[PDB]
Length: 188
Length: 182
Image (cartoon, rainbow over all chains, first blue to last red):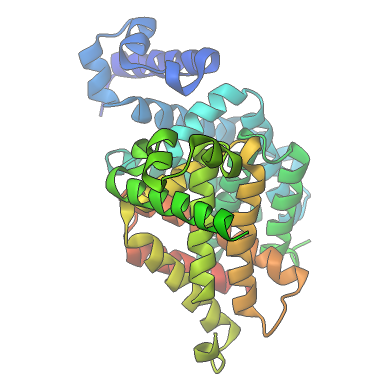
């Protein structure tokens, strides 16, 4: 399904969405402005992404997909599940902390995305869960996927506290370390 | 004092009435003050912003749920915690617009409302921590409760947006509880 022309259009649309959110945050991300920056027809934009929530959640899914594909796992080749999980948690954290305004825009879209964006939210959730489950495992068990979901929930809550300046990066790291210990502490 | 407690009550009652009608967007400072029959200044003294107002309203909801144990003595820590989760789930599901208003304020509350957010988090964590204990909980139980509160918030957001059914939410919290305490 699809074409090289469609993949090229989608890449430009998401690049434009991220460029606009990096400069002016969630509020700056508007359909007309994104269409103009990506050099795509507004109608074509609406067809692939029916709203700014769809654009931002799709940009977030692409970002997690890139982190997953590009993270060098040789660094923890001889590490324990506890170390591998803390490594991936640390990698996702540093990636989100790099551009606060952009992270804030994608997170806002993700937290309040409606049912019409279920496929885009599921792609995000499955990617983060897969990264944590594979770190704890290789091919994970159903229990490792259930643990991964809990860690993702703790990660999201702490990301929200960090974005709003209610928690420091230090506070976030300590809270995530505690959750990992409570779930798999005996795996080190 | 008496008059102060009555003024805060009227302010929070007006907030809830407005939120129940039109959600987060309907809640505005002037409208709340007029409905509560308080001066805008009295409103700002206790609640510096609409975010402080909605997060404080959320704290009163949790406090009232907490106020309303003897019936669950015979049950195990696992069963008491699942019962507490069920009560909190049902309470938030009864009035979607009111829940949406309080959740939106809680999620995006800034550093200036940190005190109110911290108090709300302590209230929900204590409800879960107390459910797993007999008497005062241990630090380990409060840490477990914080993880349960994070799972609960994530599932509440999925439920509010029609991405998870009430059954889905129940099953996910059951799984998290099982993973943490057994």
